[PDB]
Length: 35
Length: 35
Image (tube, rainbow over all chains, first blue to last red; front, side, top):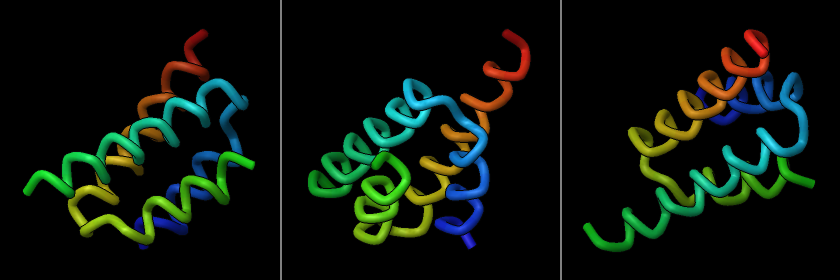
């Protein structure tokens, strides 16, 4: 499941790399709002 | 905390965009592991 699998990867990532993932999720929601 | 904030955003995303976020996390981990 996508969220559970993302949690598993993120638990291994240092905070700055987790922040990239979060900021990517925020862009994806902006793009979703433009569909 | 970044993981919970990412979950919150991902819960709003359509499944293909959730997969974008998971694949972004997987990329970050491959880079972290190669550093």
